[PDB]
Length: 431
Ligand SMILES: [Zn+2]
Image (cartoon, rainbow, N blue to C red; front, side, top):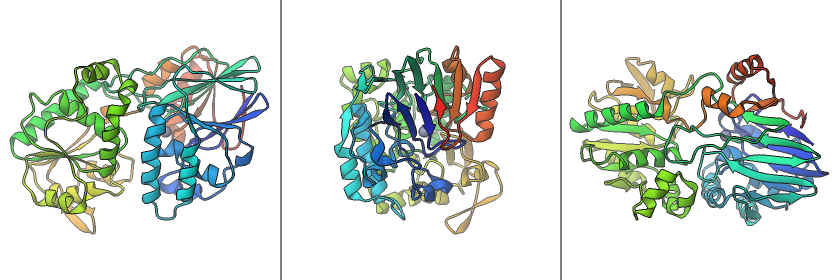
């Protein structure tokens, strides 16, 4: 039993890991590379796709399922396992990815083919390949998200996939992994813990009552997959005290994902499920409105507050959010609320630098609106949570994370008495 990193080595995108055991080949995830690494979705995998026996998907995000259609486009015809939640989500993530992409490295025939091989595998359901035993464990990072437990040849391996931030309320807490000979894990935030969730929410609510009470606009850059709906859920459970104002989810994509949420009730936390039982959708605060097209999206830039706006991209690469920022950053009464850390060098960071102006969409924009960064809405387990999850685990190979962040985690694990390594691309590791 060996596991071979084929993505997310000293980096956060590309997640794909080949497990060689029981005389079988099981591919754990198959995401694409993003941002600067995008061109690498064109390069080859590094293994023979036609030789793969089965595929397991930890969650529906593009950096975990994105290259799947390339796997089929290049031969593979085996089954692809994933929870029903990921199965349903995947279709929206993929269909959207096909429509949005400069140089697509796969076509509609591939997505179609890729989706046709999906087979439901729920938490605690065992898959039998050769003499290898596989099961999904609750990861709490996305509806239907999981980590992989693989046993065979008298040994146990655990592929964490992405672990969630247990302090939040939407998803159920990540399960502890069983004791394993080897643990391949992420370390997105191996360098630091997140600000507590409760105090992050209270701050969010103050910023909201403040700017809305003065007829101002609250601009919120958000990820369409699961960050948008979480903000909506916070707006819902606190709608009674917030000043009345429309909430524009300015994202067709976030809209599609949101419509799907009622079909996934079982994949949420107890708290969320209890709300649904009372017969009410807690992901739709009063006043929500899903803006479908450009014309209405731009009308908002010219319309007066009070209002709350959710738009992407979540890191300001592109999206409708830029347009909102362009016309709203100049008014001191508005407020920009980041609900996720902005990458260094990106426009976000540049904004947080709080200079006199910022270049957005070809023009220079005065920056008067207030700025707040609530890193506490993070979807990944922070360093402290990463440590508790990894406790008592003998050997650990880190993936998914910048080198520095991964190292900061390895140090602590090493001082704790655990054998740690930083996965290298192509270089398999023995379970
Ligand atoms: Zn990931």
